[PDB]
Amino acid sequence: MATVHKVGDSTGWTTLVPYDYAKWASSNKFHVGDSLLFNYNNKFHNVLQVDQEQFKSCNSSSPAASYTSGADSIPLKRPGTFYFLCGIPGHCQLGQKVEIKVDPG
Amino acid sequence: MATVHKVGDSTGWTTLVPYDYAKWASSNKFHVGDSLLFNYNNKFHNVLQVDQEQFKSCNSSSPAASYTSGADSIPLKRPGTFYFLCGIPGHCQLGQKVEIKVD
Amino acid sequence: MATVHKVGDSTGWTTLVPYDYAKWASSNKFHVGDSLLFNYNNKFHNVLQVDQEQFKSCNSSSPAASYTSGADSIPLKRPGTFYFLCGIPGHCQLGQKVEIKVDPGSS
Amino acid sequence: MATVHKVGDSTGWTTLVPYDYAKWASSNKFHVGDSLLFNYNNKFHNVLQVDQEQFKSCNSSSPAASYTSGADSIPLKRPGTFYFLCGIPGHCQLGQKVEIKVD
Ligand SMILES: [Cu+]
Ligand SMILES: [Cu+]
Ligand SMILES: [Cu+]
Ligand SMILES: [Cu+]
Image 1 (cartoon, rainbow over the protein chains, first blue to last red):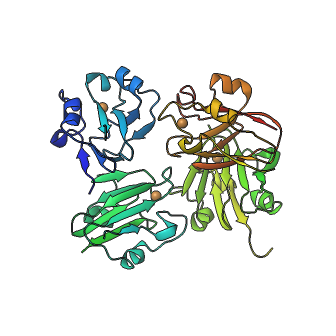
Image 2 (image 1 turned 120 degrees about the vertical axis):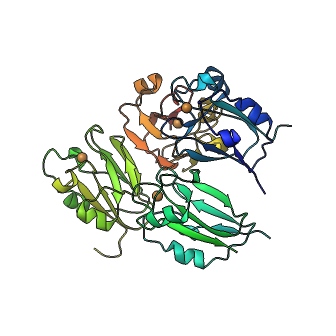
């Protein structure tokens, strides 16, 4: 049985207050088959999949994938590092971004 | 021996033709541990889990979960009745919705 | 052989003047594997795939598929009748809609 | 006499990882009568045929043709050099473009 990981737990995907999404990620163990659930007010944020370089620079100008439901379920079908961030101007820079490590050795 | 239930069989999840999803669900036996597989053109459809009220009114404004892979594998780990519909404008009203009773 | 059918030929997809897209379709023979090419100014029109009911009523509120490139290539992979129309308010009603018959049994 | 060239092989048409499409094209021999197959998640990418100038500048403003099926089968019926790129903002600049020399 796979696992659905709620990003930020009860806090969800937000910029309201500082939230260490890196620590949230490290408190979780991601396996192939699992999924991510991003809960947020879709009138304020979105979820964009980017690469390492874009993630580090909070570059949201050319995302690989985009989600805007406010309750996005995202599949983790292959091992590796995935990166997600909110593309609204200034949000990623305030910490709204998360690195997901799926089945590392 | 879990079972994967392919929603709409080969027809999949669409509005191209009328398709009786209720009848499809009835031709299936859902048990805890099983899963649902929604195959569709993800550029034009989506899969949203909603509550009974939203399902009836075809309300896709506050989904419990939104799937957009085009090949969504959704687990059935709890007994009860669950509802899914496509949130694309008017699709649910065209019949793209399905009630799933587990156990 | 797979053929790309240019909707409206040199006239393209437009509402500028009346254009009988039904006669354009009739002048063509659609076979599985073929495709349609819709040429238009994407700042003015779009291409929406709908069902028979919507086609007849020019209802563009719930299309099955949508295209907005101005040079849309659309695949015809299975036999049957497909319907397309421009969803911009009033355009379909002025004639911007086309019925595509793919590999029908009879003429 | 007739070959289907799967763009990017199993990797397909994407920006998820750097992928050398130029090298892929070079590992292939295109002859009139062949075809190109672009496999991708059609919710996030597209395939546009453009001219040399637009290809170089990654200009997707006026494509000769736009494919969005996620499994586009594009015929190569004429010898010469043709250009394709994904028009999604910034994808072409990330390397999602391919030059095809036929015959
Ligand atoms: Cu945000
Ligand atoms: Cu839909
Ligand atoms: Cu129009
Ligand atoms: Cu792309």
